[PDB]
Length: 34
Image (cartoon, rainbow, N blue to C red; front, side, top):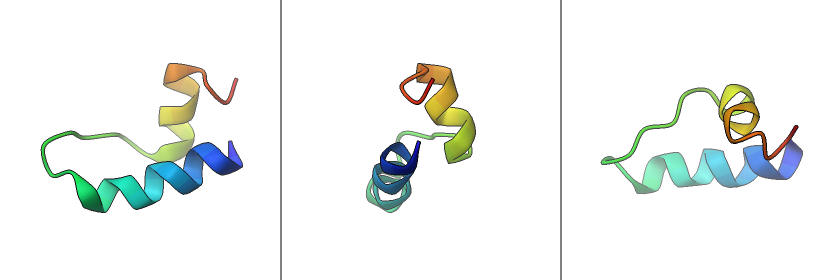
């Protein structure tokens, strides 16, 4: 989760086209964080 969050936060700025909901949630969704 830490790393997932780091990447997720930075990326948010980068793409206006795609949208990810709050990072803790996003990591669980992909379940990358588990």
